[PDB]
Image (spheres, rainbow, N blue to C red):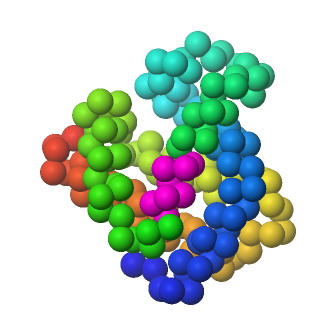
């Protein structure tokens, strides 16, 4: 788990995200899709996006970014008491969306990258450590649910 102090860092960082949730979510998704093109293929509604310019110009992608980070934010605000939020998310992504767990590692790295890119010098080592632990906890709890389902992807 995270300590009190670690959760406080996570949620302080998350205030950065919340000041521009769509812009952060867009940049996270673009980072994921350009670094790991296999991820894009899982999105029927973004798989038409051929270039980063088109990605950056898609208003639906920005909208989706808000959906994604709102769901994550609400989970992080539970400080690990997230079973009801996180179970359905896990099950949806294993059964419907067919998303390998590995893709949660990719997006965790993307979030760290984007935070440094948008907040250079304002995402220090303690904050990074705390956010990394929270994203590990998130994916670890999703992986437990994937194991229940047998789901590899």
Q: State which quadrant residue 55 falls in.
A: top right
Q: Can the viewer see residue 125 in this picture? A: yes
* Residue, far top: 48
Which span is picked out in magenta? 69-76
Q: Is residue 18 above or below residue 64?
A: below
Q: Is residue 42 above or below residue 86?
A: above
Residue 102 spot, x, y in % from top left = 40, 45
| 123 relative position to 79: left or right | right
Residue 91 spot, x, y in % from top left = 27, 43
Residue 85 spot, x, y in % from top left = 35, 55
Q: Residue at x 83, y 62 (%)?
A: 120
| 37 relative position to 127: left or right | left
Rendered-image quadrant of the C terminus: top left
Q: Residue at x 67, y 38 (%)?
A: 26
Q: Can the viewer see residue 55 in this picture? A: no
Q: Residue at x 30, y 58 (%)?
A: 84
Please give the count of numbered marks on the rendered protein.
0
* Residue, far right: 121
Rendered-image quadrant of the N terminus: bottom left
Q: Main secondary structure of the magenta part?
A: helix
| 123 relative position to 42: left or right | right
Magenta stretch encompasses residue 146: no
For the residue pair 24 and 32, the one nearer the viewer reads as: 24
Magenta stretch encompasses residue 72: yes
Q: Is residue 101 above or below residue 123?
A: above
Residue 64 spot, x, y in % from top left = 58, 34
| 114 relative position to 72: left or right | right
Q: Residue at x 47, y 18 (%)?
A: 44
């Amino acid at each position: 788990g995270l300590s009190d102090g670690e959760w406080q860092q996570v949620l302080n960082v998350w205030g950065k995200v919340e000041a521009d949730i769509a812009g952060h979510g867009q940049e996270v998704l673009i980072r994921l899709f350009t670094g790991h093109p296999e991820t894009l293929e899982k999105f029927d509604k973004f798989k038409h996006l051929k270039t980063e310019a088109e990605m950056k110009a898609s208003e639906d992608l920005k909208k989706h970014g808000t959906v994604v980070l709102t769901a994550l934010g609400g989970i992080l605000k539970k400080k690990g008491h997230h079973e009801a939020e996180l179970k359905p998310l896990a099950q949806s992504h294993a059964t419907k969306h067919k998303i390998p767990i590995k893709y949660l590692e990719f997006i965790s790295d993307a979030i760290i990258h984007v935070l440094h890119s948008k907040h250079p010098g304002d995402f220090g080592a303690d904050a990074q450590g705390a956010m990394t632990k929270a994203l590990e906890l998130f994916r670890n709890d999703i992986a437990a649910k994937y194991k229940e389902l047998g789901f590899q992807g």
